[PDB]
Length: 281
Ligand SMILES: COc1ccc2c(-c3ccc(C(=O)O)c(C4CCCC4)c3)ccnc2c1
Image 1: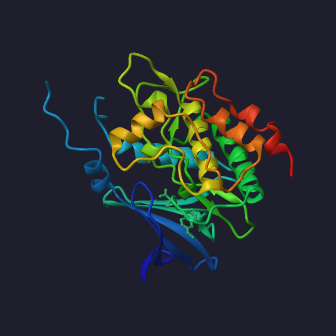
Image 2: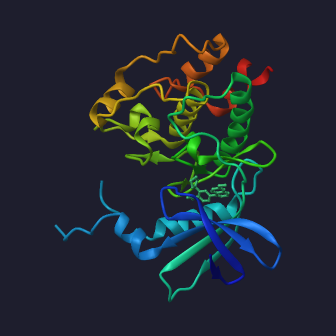
C-alpha cells in the first residue's frame, strides 16, 4: 500500500475512461472510500498533440477534468456516485478524487453469458431512470451510459459512475455537432457525416436502451468487430431480439421505443418512467 495524507491506498478496484480507481482507507473516520488517481500531464496527452496554426481540438484539454469535478460537486442523489474530496496541489502533477465506496462494483461487463433476469433488470433500470432524470434536471448529460459504469452498492441499488466525459449544458438541451462514447452504445444520429446537430439527452436515452438490452441478453443489439460495420448496423440494421431467453412483449416495446433510430420520435425519460413494463412487478 501507500499513504496519501489521511488515506491508505490499496488494490485497484476499477479503471474507467481516465486514470485508475483504488480502494482507500481513511484513518480519520475508519472508513473505506474509492479514490480515482489521475495525472494532469497524461490527461493533456490523451487529447492528442496540438496542431500547428493553419472536429477542432479543445485549446485547453485539462479543462474537462475540472468540468467533471464541478459536475460531481453539483450532484447529490442515491443513484449517482458521491464525490467527497478532491486532493490537488497546483505544483504537483497528480489529482485525486475521493468517492463514497459502492461495494460490489460494476453490475455487468458486456458481453456476459450470465444476463440478469427480467425482474432484476427492472429493479436496476428503475434506479437508472431515477439517476438519469436527476442528471438531466441538473443540466448534465452523462454520455457514457453502459452497464460497466453502473456500480452496485451494499443495498442492491445501482449508482451511475464515470463522469469523465459528462457535460453540463445551458438551456433546455445540449446541442452537439459530434460526441464521445463507447461505439456500441452511440446513437445513430451521432455516427454520420451530416450538416445537422443533435440532442444530447436523446443520446443518453439511446444508451439506456442498449444498456437495458444488455441487462437481459448479456450483449448489445448491434455488434460487429469491424468498426465501420458496427456503425453501419447501428444506423441501418433493424432491432431484433434473440429467440431465447424469451422476454415480455412490454419490455420489447420499451426497448424498441428507446432504440428508435429517429431521435425526434424516440421515447423521452418522463415517458419511460410511466411505461407499463417499468410500473409493474
Ligand atoms: C468496488 O469497485 C468500485 C470501483 C469503482 C468505484 C468508484 C469509481 C470512481 C470513479 C470512476 C471513474 O473512472 O470516474 C469509476 C469508474 C471505473 C470503472 C467503473 C466506473 C468508479 C466509485 C465508488 N465506488 C467504486 C467501487
